[PDB]
Length: 281
Image (tube, rainbow, N blue to C red):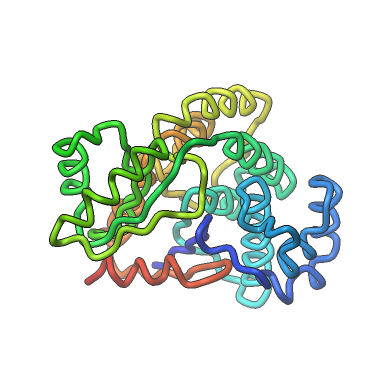
């Protein structure tokens, strides 16, 4: 069986979507009309360093991932057995699955980006060398119970998330731990996928109520639950995604467990492919 995997924030790169904007001119134009700027310009020239600001990053990745998908299936007229995507990427899996059309998904990710960009005074950090359980234990025992686990990416790669000052203290703590091989703050000023996104989540959930979804035709493994979406559960699972951990390791393991599974990353970069390899070994 095969799974298609869609990248999220962390995979954006200037030059992404290279060949595709010209090949899908109508879609790019539709995006530009909706967003108020040129998507080609954003991705290729990274004006004002906008590619790295979440309100731009999210729709940029969404659009590149869509065009990457449409191109892939234009050349190879195969549909995957499953799809998943990392945070932002989950919108691309839902699109591949037919839950919504292109512009619907673009509206949702534009709003998601906007709300998340309103977070300040937060930070996130990638922690390598420890299991999720060990990271959680370390947080609790060093007075850092206020920090959440935002991503569980592979068995020894976790991203933590919380108030700026708490993430600062955490650096010290983790650098003193022998098995930690890396502590690397990420380039955000919000504590994404944490309790500190409560407001954004509730605003997004309210926004969601205006939308109606179509049938999921390819199972989508949710970040929140590491299990397929249920047709009637799209609203709640998309809203929960904002303030809950991305259970990426468990999502991949769910897929591995079904037997002989291959994965292909659709979108820029090889980040998720790299994670597969660490999950398997």
